[PDB]
Image 1: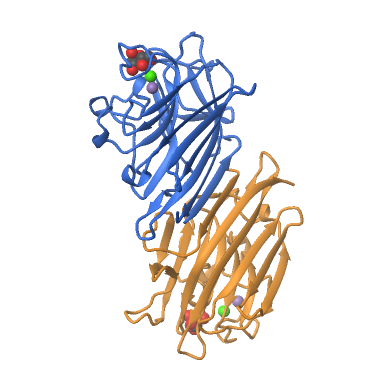
Image 2: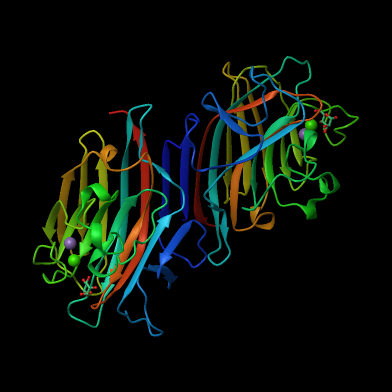
Length: 240
Length: 240
Ligand SMILES: OC[C@H]1O[C@H](O)[C@@H](O)[C@@H](O)[C@@H]1O
Ligand SMILES: OC[C@H]1O[C@H](O)[C@@H](O)[C@@H](O)[C@@H]1O
Ligand SMILES: [Ca+2]
Ligand SMILES: [Ca+2]
Ligand SMILES: [Mn+2]
Ligand SMILES: [Mn+2]
């Protein structure tokens, strides 16, 4: 289809169109990307991702068209630790994408250690909300919590300072305009605090014509829940 | 998802989200539901169907909601014969539906011969565009071409006389309003000739909560091409 849209105002346990990978599962009408024990507390060493089952037609070689897409979602992170980790990301990848071996912790379930900073070795565009930046292990990160735009590498092409707020929902709107090739991210907390970051990228040179969209999160030695609360997505092919 | 929408203005050969069954295949930017020969001519004894791959949440018991949905599509029928057969149908059925054994010809690839008129044995709602009605083999049909609403039986609960026009595209809008439980069908040719048929039906008592939607067509001894040219669909769960 040239156009596709879907909306999850909440996530009831009865799901048919989500691909669950790793530890991801539905609990209390939300998607818990990372594992929680019986009491709902976060645990270490866990990775989980979800993908929408239908493939999205991102661009079409034959017709010179590229999709205009918008992804709106909300999530919250909670941890009793002072340094909850590692973060959650909205991502776009080839349809057969699976969790790479050893992609836990700071790799966010998106990259393999050996090629995490090798741009010619990956095909992924992701928007990360990264809460762990210890310079000794997450050497590629700026030294503070941040929102980053990742294009084929865990070392973000761009980051902006962000504040992690325990148990508070962050609403995010990610949009891509094929005319300007701008990928824009706008995130807000309920008190109006706003974060914005934009990057120009030709998706046709990074991803295949058909892709799958979803979310990924992970926790290494440090941990926190990564709860996806709602998600709506729309995409339509346009002449450029 | 509570809401789902997709649009196919045309059908390029590179499809990823369609389930093809029987003889259905893409050809010249359209879906040819029934088999054609090397030159594009329709042939006898063929059945074909397509279904969109993502499942539609038609109703939700826990919340007492039922979806409002709209399906718009256009198709054309062509045949060397003056009495082409057998017809095309838009249908909604359980997700695992497959072509029933012996469902060719007048059964339109939707019902099994032995239970075609047994309402307690089927789970399907279909809107048929039936061009063949000989009473020796299609004993359940009115004696004229017709559009019909089928609820668990090949013997339509409601029909309207219709005119088959060789090679002309018919534009169809099928809508279901949960507030009134009315399934409405409006079909029009480009010159403005219009046909309408509606029926009140509680989808909750006929189909499961999750379903798949698609099209089916067949040709028995008499034949014609059944070309699906475009298709758009949208569904939204509503409390009514
Ligand atoms: O969880 C914090 C931290 O723990 C370990 O050091 C590794 O798993 C890192 O990749 C991760 O960033
Ligand atoms: O095609 C016309 C007619 O041919 C045969 O008689 C059978 O396949 C019927 O079911 C069909 O309606
Ligand atoms: Ca990090
Ligand atoms: Ca018939
Ligand atoms: Mn980072
Ligand atoms: Mn009929």
